[PDB]
Length: 285
Length: 282
Image 1 (cartoon, each protein chain N blue to C red):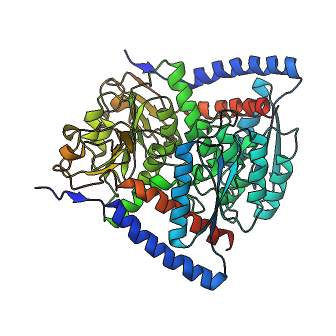
Image 2 (image 1 turned 90 degrees about the horizontal axis):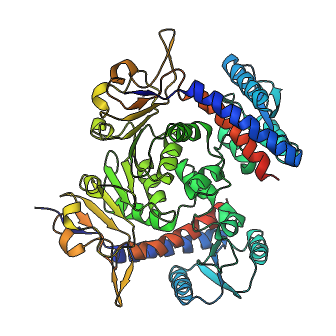
Image 3 (image 1 turned 90 degrees about the vertical axis):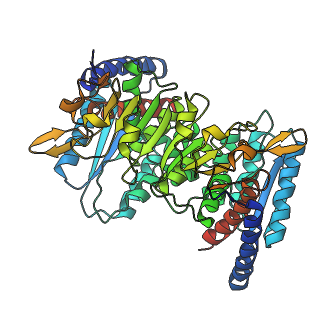
């Protein structure tokens, strides 16, 4: 028989937001500082407006201030860098986020590099990426990988000496989560689209992290009995949201598994909130 | 049919190729790359390393300058000097010879170097840039050298299974990231890994960086493996690899000897990095 525990992100995110709200009010009482997030959106992309809206709603829930600066699509990179320079030097702003994607005429990496690492709440600045790997403590960690580790921590999933296989090598998820796992003393394998015999790896994993954006890609035969399975996929399939793991099939095999929806997805914005609070406190240390 | 991955011969060839590239660049731009190296104190091994880096610069036509500070130099004094060099446009590459004295915080010193002059590649921005595939990255010299060895010897990395033994910041983590960028499936193992052998015995490419003499035995290696030994262990008056070479050599497809394998590639890649700094600065 297997544990078949549901790693419930919706309930965990709710608990974590309530916990954070309490801390934010404590901090405000001690310092009169309310953490403030500035989100920059360039242009009109509909999905981008929705993402930003969800971020502001989450802020309001926990008592964090937010401001959205909407710039026209025709904004140049130099103009956006100018705005970010003003935000970097504005002590009322603790966390700066640039909603992706940016217009064709702007290079996102130049934009991210212009953000003070201490205000880079997404954890995408090269210094934060590097500090993650280098186990340095000023690091703003990327929200989705941080969220994954938070689930593992709160569910008591031991990482030390565990064999973890991460399927997908993206910058936003796969590579930073592999680095977080390795810092947590797991043995880590990172697989991707050039991996031959993927199943030979995934079937040995104690902890299996799936981040490929391919609906129902990971099937039962690819997962180890007693495995912990974390499904980062958010695939839109005919109005439904479906994960990268064939949940119906795999759930009977596992010690624990994240459903989709209601698994990793809500943890991403939750960790953004914690990262905003981290920015405010460390700027004012 | 075993291949010796010979770093001494490869380093010589690579320096000849670089010397020509540096001369071509100078013809077109009148710019000659310049490396500044700082040494704090008098550690004789540190002095020998810095002397080897100056010699290597001279061999390829790169300018070098060594600034020697006394052992009691304060962290603030060293950071002042680094700031000056950051902002000197005659200086393309800055390096600080390690180890620093115990009273100075290495990480603060490294952070203070401009990333685009940080030839050793351990600034956090360079570490992140490597993972991000940002072309402005200065890749750390030993991991870069390991990848160069694989490339020059025609070792296939796309779809290869690579196991990296040792998860150090200086070698194991960056080399794993380079291997992933090169399209290998990569496992990173360390002192907390259980059943190490179940991984290492499957590796098509085995990179070993544990600083333990003769640590990897024949039973830990796959037949036909390509083995890269980053160990330089001083023991029994001898320099010994992390791999038991005599024990594994008759079963591998290729292996780096120690000495004469990875060691020489480290300074070679320093010179390449110094030339990278000169071209991007301009």
